[PDB]
Length: 235
Image (cartoon, rainbow, N blue to C red):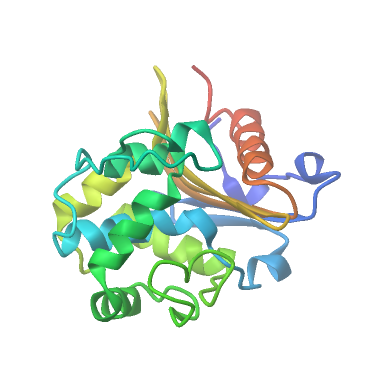
């Protein structure tokens, strides 16, 4: 009764949404892809880039750990959850862009470019500016390239320190149930939505990448519906 990802079908979940979905079974080494053409199209990563930003920032000690506090300046920004003191981990959870812009400025161009080159991270183009390049700007990456990177993060086959990789994966936890742990990060801009991450169950471990012509919230809802359908999200 164990999941064979090659027999999946997600047509129903995408009935009224243009998008792509990738699920990689880490232990069997098997992948399901819906809409391979779209999976190959590069797009701006938006806030899915926080995963990379956090890895590089911890690696070069621009931030100390998931609890490194940056005080809010008191400026009311677009979402109330941004208008508070944040840590590296809480700013990932709430997608507080201002925190990760300060982090990118501290990382700086040279270290950002060098470490981004180790990840095969799409076109690796940061010319849009040190604190702007992942936000509807120069950097683009395809869903397949996101999957390849996240698979290497899951396997810790990246040149980062191992504790750095474990901290960033922990910061991505969205739900810890009795029988599964869901990891993920959303991105959204101009009718393109991402939800990328991992799910660990009692019987397997998986990487997923979802990208849609809709919000990141929609991308996440589609992903959760698929993972529920195939019994990976239960309780």
